[PDB]
Image 1: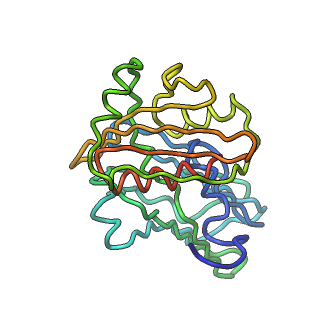
Image 2 (image 1 turned 90 degrees about the horizontal axis):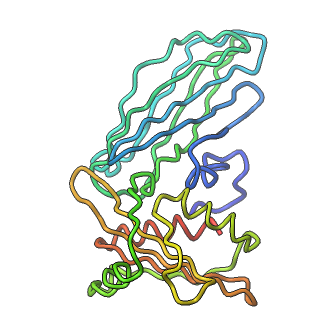
Amino acid sequence: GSPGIRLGSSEDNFARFVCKNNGVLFENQLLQIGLKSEFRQNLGRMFIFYGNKTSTQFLNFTPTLICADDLQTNLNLQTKPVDPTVDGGAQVQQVVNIECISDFTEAPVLNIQFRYGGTFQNVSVKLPITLNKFFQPTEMASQDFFQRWKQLSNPQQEVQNIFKAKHPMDTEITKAKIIGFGSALLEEVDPNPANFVGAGIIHTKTTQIGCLLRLEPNLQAQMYRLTLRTSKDTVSQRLCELLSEQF
């Protein structure tokens, strides 16, 4: 990724929004940007809240969405303009309508420009619209899970990652993280009681991708082995990257 200290960067808090949909995405001494998102099928609706932390009204308040050319073909974002004048202490809301066309890895960038005290202010932050947001959890019996797991033939469709735990192995937190990620969390499927098994379908306009995941904790080494088996190589890769950063 991008080298150097990531503090005051465009992605300081991006990671906290992969498994949850609400929270403060960015905050400086003048503005606070909060989010509330909801997804269904291959669609999403993200409410962006711009809070004026001062006692002075902002002018020319202009939020613009910026997506790489490649991203634009896989993700369609639409929004209505917000009023350019924001009173001090006020919070204005912007709604972004999202339509996932095909699977994607990049993230849109929200750029906000405004005038405060006669000065030009500029902020750019990555919006947490990630592939997993388009998940439909799919509950299924142990037998059905194993039958599907064993239907994978393409080696590219399986992605494994063995990594060090960033957080304590708190069972309940882990279960909550997996459910927040988007897939169904299947209870009592893997013969080893320490492992977590998940299943879901990633929805896009052009294709529906069945996904299976297995998370195996190594308590002594404080490491995890995450395996993704999906019907599309690029989805297995993206989902494995995203989920690995959460434990």
